[PDB]
Image (spheres, rainbow, N blue to C red):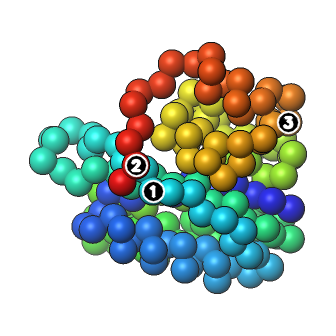
Amino acid sequence: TVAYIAIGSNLASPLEQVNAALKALGDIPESHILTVSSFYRTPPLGPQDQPDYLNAAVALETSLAPEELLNHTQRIELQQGRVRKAERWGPRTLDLDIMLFGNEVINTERLTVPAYDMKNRGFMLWPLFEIAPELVFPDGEMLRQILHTRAFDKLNKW
């Protein structure tokens, strides 16, 4: 199954944090990284003297159950992020989001797929479009269509 994961990092030097995250992702059991989008850039939240967020999309082939994949993304966030020496929601941390899992729709307390409100998030949709231009959501909605009809903030590459 092809799962699509969104990477978000505004910690230290994002470039090497995203690279450490990609290595962790590729080490996930029963999983193989198909492709990685270009790195995209978004402004910090709060003080503007912060680092920009580095955003990216990853196509990951996997035989893991959705919840098993979530387990590992959550583990990597803890191991790579700064949760121990900071806060869970800490300003500068690592975000791994399961945007899509095959053509599956998952509505449960622990995991929502497609990721809730991702269709309104350009920093997720644009990188996803770069690696999967023909992508269609489970509800039949085409990615290319959403990008033509919804208003998004400007998204420059890193």
Residue at which label 1 appears:
39
Residue occupying image coordinates x 44% and y 68%: 18
State how far apart marks 3 and 2 are (Cα): 28 Å
Residue at which label 2 appears:
157
Residue at which label 3 appears:
138
Q: Amino acid at mark 1?
A: Phe
Q: Is residue 98 visible?
A: no
Q: Position of residue 7 (x, y in %)?
A: 51, 57
Left or right: where does residue 122 sit relative to residue 49? right
Q: Amino acid at mark 2?
A: Lys
Instruction: Determine the image quadrant of residue 113.
Output: top right
Sequence order check: which comes first, mark 1 or mark 3? 1
For the residue pair 37 and 96, the one nearer the viewer reads as 37
Circle nearer the viewer, 3 or 2: 2
Q: Are marks 3 and 2 in contact (CB under 8 Å)?
A: no
Dot 1 alpha-carbon crowd within 10 angstroms: few under 14, some 14 to 19, many 20 or more = some
Sequence order check: which comes first, mark 3 or mark 2? 3
Q: Are marks 1 and 2 in contact (CB under 8 Å)?
A: yes
State how far apart marks 1 and 3 are (Cα): 26 Å
Q: Position of residue 82 (x, y in %)?
A: 34, 68
Number of numbered discs present?
Answer: 3
Left or right: where does residue 64 sit relative to residue 80? right
Left or right: where does residue 93 sit relative to residue 127? left
Residue occupying image coordinates x 84% and y 52%: 102
Sequence order check: which comes first, mark 1 or mark 2? 1
Residue occupying image coordinates x 33% and y 64%: 14
Residue occupying image coordinates x 12% and y 47%: 49
